[PDB]
Image 1 (cartoon, rainbow, N blue to C red):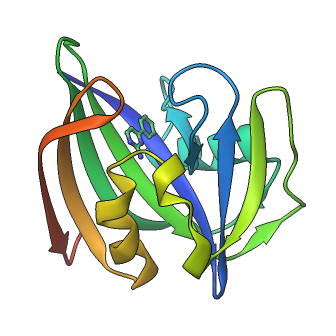
Image 2 (image 1 turned 120 degrees about the horizontal axis):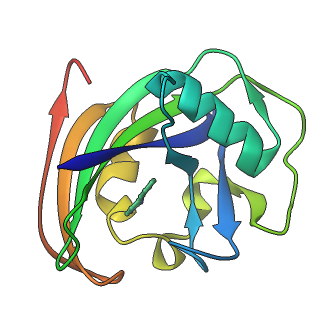
Image 3 (image 1 turned 90 degrees about the vertical axis):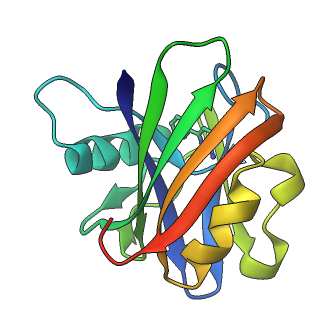
Length: 154
Ligand SMILES: Nc1nccc(-c2ccccc2)n1
């Protein structure tokens, strides 16, 4: 019914790293780093791998911050996105053919050029709150319905 994905936010005291995807799902938007979890791989190991593949950064500890289920009307598979954050990274962000990373000051997060759901849950991430969310999309731009609640255990 649902497919596992990861999403990683590199969140430091005064800035956050986002990546501009050049192609595929979500191209043209700033977003966290992530993708599909593989066979035999833990969700956290998948999150660490995708962060390296897409940003060039090596993460140690990842902290669970949320879970968001996305439904796209007309598509059978739900996306079960496990969201993580970290403030301890090594390496410097790498631009590739697939992704352009850039740091943003927290007061300059580019919500108009991000997925629309981020405007709801990013403020929770910034205040170190954990959450469970569900967003029903029509296409890539329109949220038909959603739920979002803070939780103690992701
Ligand atoms: N912010 C946002 N909105 C919609 C979808 C996603 C997503 C993230 C990781 C993997 C698959 C989808 N992220």
